Amino acid sequence: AGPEMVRGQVFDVGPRYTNLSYIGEGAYGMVCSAYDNVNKVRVAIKKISPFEHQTYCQRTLREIKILLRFRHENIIGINDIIRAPTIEQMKDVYIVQDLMETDLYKLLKTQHLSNDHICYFLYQILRGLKYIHSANVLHRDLKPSNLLLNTTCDLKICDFGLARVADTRWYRAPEIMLNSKGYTKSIDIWSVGCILAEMLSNRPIFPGKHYLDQLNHILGILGSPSQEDLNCIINLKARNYLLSLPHKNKVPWNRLFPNADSKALDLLDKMLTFNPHKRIEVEQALAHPYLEQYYDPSDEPIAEAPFKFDMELDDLPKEKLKELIFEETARFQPGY
Ligand SMILES: Cn1nccc1Nc1nccc(-c2ccn([C@H](CO)c3ccc(Cl)c(F)c3)c(=O)c2)n1
């Protein structure tokens, strides 16, 4: 027969995985669904081709190590990994995962959510995030397309390529745009607030077309930052820009979302706080009155131990990273 092919991309995952169907693609990979002839279900398969770039190698290794370590209902797992039998021949890595029927990006393009579903999705996002943060990990790229949903409204967070151990513009915290890397766990909470806003209105709350436009969108709702807000390490260009702007008035949340649950808007206000030091943390968010019908501290697992990378990944040449990826994936090879 041959390896199957999808949109030009070779998908060399047979014979176990067949009947491929395109799901989507990114800068250095493609995601398809496939039929698994061992477990007799359809699965997701992400083809990644990262080896020409140190950055892409980092992401690939980080996602693999983190997802194989993590164990939580609201976090996607890895069931299988396919790659070449020799490192010389390995140009692609195929990561096999439970197939989810859709993502929140797609869902919000087509469906108006009930307040009860918004509440339940938010709960699951934060429940998963509680586990991530308890492992001392930052996800750093939370957004609707990284929130997977199955047929019965189960939610799983995916794509941990940008994850980092502590110590997409539209969903990026202010600190990110103010700092050349100077931020914390709170950046994830900002992203979740953006996602909550988007679930309330079916449109991105801060859809900036570029960096400056993103800052202007944020201040367009929060208003000009205070002195306290600007009492931090900030990029000089960004600080000067902000100081050059006209005054902007704060827009009350109930004016932007006139039909939203008042409790939902109270939580939204605490997540979309400019100053990350005054921004609500994940446990406090779970305990917020908006989530009272789902909050269950007896059933919200945390990680057994903090997550730790054994090597300074940023320092490693991409060739060493490829060797680590070969090693991490060896356990899925026959005869291991
Ligand atoms: C049917 N459908 N529609 C949307 C999602 C799904 N189902 C599904 N099921 C399991 C896993 C995944 C899935 C998707 C996207 N991603 C990231 C999203 O950022 C991703 C990284 C790299 C590249 Cl190249 C990519 F295209 C997507 C995952 O990691 C994992 N999706």
Image (cartoon, grey):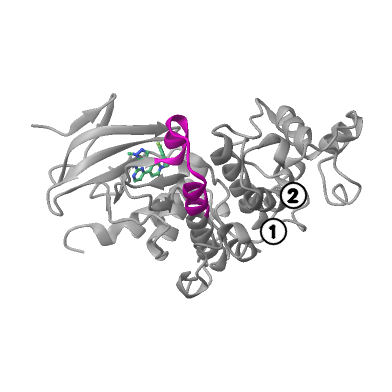
Q: Quadrant of the C terminus?
A: bottom left
Name the element at disc 2.
Answer: loop
Q: Are marks 1 and 2 in contact (CB under 8 Å)?
A: yes
Residue 4 appears in view: yes
Left or right position of 20 against 205: left
**Residue 35 falls in which quadrant of the image?**
top left
Quadrant of ligand 1: it is: top left
For badge 2, the amino acid type reads Thr
Task: Identify the residue at image location x=59%, y=33%.
Answer: 204
Q: Which mark is residue 280?
A: 1
Q: CA distance from mark 1 to mark 2?
A: 8 Å
Name the element at disc 1.
Answer: loop
Residue 207 position (above or below residue 135): above
Region rendered in magenta? 103-122
> Of callouts 1 and 2, which one flags the residue occurring earlier in the amino acid sequence?
2
Residue 99 sits inside the magenta stretch: no
Where does the image place residue 28, in percent across and percent down from the top left?
A: 42, 35
Residue 54 appears in view: no
Task: Identify the residue at image location x=47%, y=56%.
Answer: 124
Residue 40 position (above or below residue 31): below
Left or right position of 188 against 16: right
Residue 106 position (above or below residue 191): above
Where does the image place residue 192, in percent across and percent down from the top left?
A: 59, 49
Label 2 residue near ligand 1, CB within 8 Å: no
Q: Which residue is mark 2?
A: 273
For badge 1, the amino acid type reads Ile
Where does the image place residue 294, in percent across and percent down from the top left?
A: 49, 62
**Residue 333 falls in which quadrant of the image?**
bottom left
| Residue nearest the viewer, comparing 68 with 227 | 227
Q: Which mark is residue 47?
A: none
Where does the image place residue 214, in percent across and percent down from the top left?
A: 70, 32
Task: Identify the residue at image location x=64%, y=58%.
Answer: 185
